[PDB]
Image 1: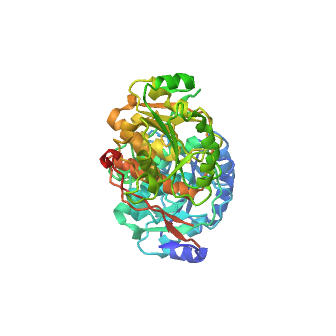
Image 2 (image 1 turned 45 degrees about the horizontal axis):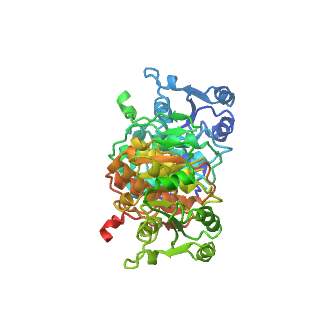
Image 3 (image 1 turned 120 degrees about the vertical axis):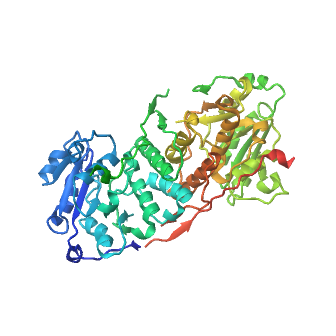
Length: 276
Length: 276
């Protein structure tokens, strides 16, 4: 079920909640330039469609936290989200921890590096969960995605061709039921999105998954070497889901030449349910 | 064994041949703009260090063949290289066929899409084969390689971390013994380079492999979608070498949106030896 153009009104969607709550999480690591625009794009929904909004500050050392606070957002460190458990690096750790710092029946993730995101992102993502049947996960897609098109989609075609129809498997913008998310392990680092998608599919099949058009995403764009490490972790997570042993050996890069090895992790966090 | 700066003279290298011959192959599909510069970069070696030079025209429909002929090169179609066998599409087919159209003890491959290549490429590549011991394969590297850094090297780190030290595993510029090449299967399409590298390693280990610095490669650069299909075949070939089953399902791309599926092949050509 793919929406190329949503149309629900905020008021329709709110009516459709039927006692269900909605939390929104913005994970953030050093996004001082864009965080404020993102928070402002969503905060008008708070106390209405959105019951709760947090910024999960993931170790920022710039002005991310102060600017987020000044935009009226509740800011939660990785440590505060789950203080009994020492913090590991990477995005996946942050999202997993964010489940402990929220209580919505529905959880929405939005990356904090978006440049002026549309204020209907959140309504568009929750639409299928609210008005559909059996949808537990909603992915975004949009209109240059080097990792997505060179790494994730081609590996999916190779190893889970059934997910070939997912236009943006690595998309940082998505929503899901708490019941699903707290039932799934969380891959480390940049592996978290692909892991959630494959795990969701393996457990519930395609009928539990939707994808919605958010139009065009401005963000961006990153250095090649950081993409290398990201790809490595995506590969590691994807191979693991396909029953394939990963060496655990980090990508090395040669910058004569000097060498650098990036970390990779083969350790998922378990379902947040076990932490109950 | 890695050379960051070769220094053999053409005359030293020629002396070192010791009865061994050298063939050079330029595979070409629609490279009318660059082919002439490449042929000219190498033809001064002919009847000296290089005993034989061919262009393997791989179905070009531009002026590639006429311009190559006008540069004094022997041009060989896929059909002429091996006429008893119907032609399949893709680069790997062309290189495999080129073994039947050459007779050098040493074979050098140079892509025909290079912009003004250095005239010492060929001497630099054959150096380790000529003056080394046990080298059977020489890869080039150089000073943006999206597929190499996002797909091939990270998958190698995952599945053959021993080949992590190869800076340009997908490089189209390399040399090898006929004995090796005619003993190896040839992967289809864009899988051919990675297949030869992994097969070489699995059979002879690293000590049979060298890599040499050619400096800087200008070529280039391609549309994202063509890179998608290339990555898919590289993945398919690499998974196969690692004992991993590939779906055989082609990458689909969505250009509302229209869909296109690119071909992928799980069929290698066998060792050219069997064709004897």
